[PDB]
Amino acid sequence: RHMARIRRSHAILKSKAMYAALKGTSWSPDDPVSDYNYYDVWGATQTTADVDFTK
Amino acid sequence: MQNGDFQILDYTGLISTMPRVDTLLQSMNLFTEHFGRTTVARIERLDDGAGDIKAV
Image (tube, rainbow over all chains, first blue to last red; front, top):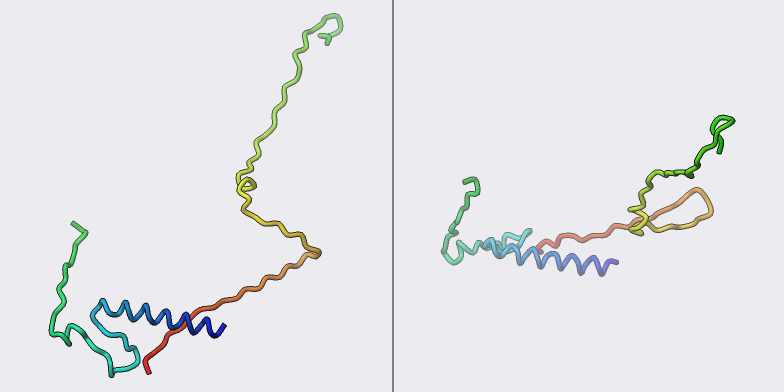
């Protein structure tokens, strides 16, 4: 039972880390050392194609 | 038959009717039947999950 819990906990973390990449940030929830912001690191910006459904 | 006392009749049989009964659910075999011995039943349930893994 404990082994299965450990496996599932690692699997969840992998998916969360992969998701965190798209938003342009590294995943290090409890550590400021490796908390990178890629837009800042590479010197870029985020463009927004906001869509309005009300019209 | 006999109408009154001095007259006769023609007899045409009987008519019968019954109400409706629905059997939709029984046709779906959705339930399972168990036969016990006493009027008390016990059920046990188990839950499991996962957790977070923070950086170290």
